[PDB]
Image (cartoon, rainbow, N blue to C red; front, side, top):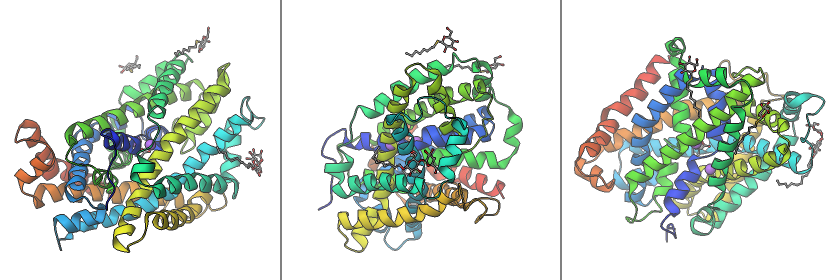
Length: 441
Ligand SMILES: CCCCCCCCCCCCO[C@@H]1O[C@H](CO)[C@@H](O[C@H]2O[C@H](CO)[C@@H](O)[C@H](O)[C@H]2O)[C@H](O)[C@H]1O
Ligand SMILES: CCCCCCCCS[C@@H]1O[C@H](CO)[C@@H](O)[C@H](O)[C@H]1O
Ligand SMILES: CCCCCCCCS[C@@H]1O[C@H](CO)[C@@H](O)[C@H](O)[C@H]1O
Ligand SMILES: N[C@@H](Cc1ccccc1)C(=O)O
Ligand code: NA
Ligand code: NA
């Protein structure tokens, strides 16, 4: 008795709701800032076109054909073949990513609370920077808001696909977009527009000499597209043949890129106007945006609206993150949805506590040489499991399927686009991920 999307637009809006989240604003900004900007952006955009869209369609095709979880899709379509490692890696990536994703979303709820209680209407005495560092260094305060955000995530996933995940408000994502556009226009009028736009669109190829820039670009591309972990396999597994998968993949990647680019047009001209370093780090948007809201007269209102709509997008993205282990645990151990959502959601919440403490008392600890627990967990998930999982997924359709089956199940003919998509999965995307891997070591 597997669930299905009740409405016709349920699938595409859920995929869009999974893609558009904290990766478009919070992560895109601080990764672009510390990687040089425009040159990193063009590689990132190229990764979205030639690798992201094909592998997104790949995950859709696997999910709808198999009607199973991320791991079960490989067992059903290729029994006893080693392709199921991608789903296994993807389930574990759901644990690691959601562990720290709920921490950052806990920052969102905390800032929303401070605007609703009138705390951040004016600049605190310690400054918008010192206020942010004092809150993340506090050992217990972020955990309370992290747990609060996880309770919402657990609640939606436990309610179900039809009654929970699908029942997301269809105005919040367009309202987030309209506000980002309105905010991007305003930051262009703050004085740092020339150097901010040059940093974002005028590329310096000297940064591309580093192989690590390519690894950050492929990681952000996979991360922002909810790609390489079976998250799109799971949402595709609730779709009937009613849908057209090609247009869904292009619309998902096209909308996700628009959110990211406009976020950069909002953030970076504001960074230069404030004279701050764009390589500030994970708290970049949390220091820049409240300082931009403070310059507006109706600033507190924009801040309340911004963090509500951003938290709403973070909620729908964390739901798809939790859905991957929930669906896998329901099939494998015959767990109910409620027990899988509660038990796995509690475990993931505790897993993220050490990464939350990395910003404070555990700042000295390393796991991956030179990286704290937060950066170590983000690195193995975003830079290792997602690109490798996406590489295996591309090779699965490219070399483990019949060509006619790959095109027919993906709603494509043997046309120029059908051949371009098969070429990407067989060669272009896997070799690109492979070359990015090898050069980074
Ligand atoms: C959006 C959903 C809202 C539902 C939740 C509503 C109930 C919220 C309960 C209030 C919890 C507030 O808890 C209290 O917060 C304030 C800051 O806000 C902290 O007060 C102080 O502590 C920390 C550092 O110690 C500082 O970052 C902060 O600037 C300072 O004001 C208290 O140390 C904390 O105990
Ligand atoms: C629908 C969204 C439209 C948003 C437009 C916001 C532009 C704000 S103008 C404002 O005028 C001042 C001088 O008059 C300058 O000093 C400021 O730098 C500048 O910010
Ligand atoms: C939504 C607003 C979009 C604005 C896009 C601006 C892209 C041009 S940036 C950069 O600015 C410098 C100005 O001198 C030049 O040196 C560079 O050649 C040029 O590339
Ligand atoms: N795409 C989400 C992050 C995500 C990754 C993997 C699965 C689901 C969601 C974002 O950009 O916020
Ligand atoms: Na995204
Ligand atoms: Na979202």
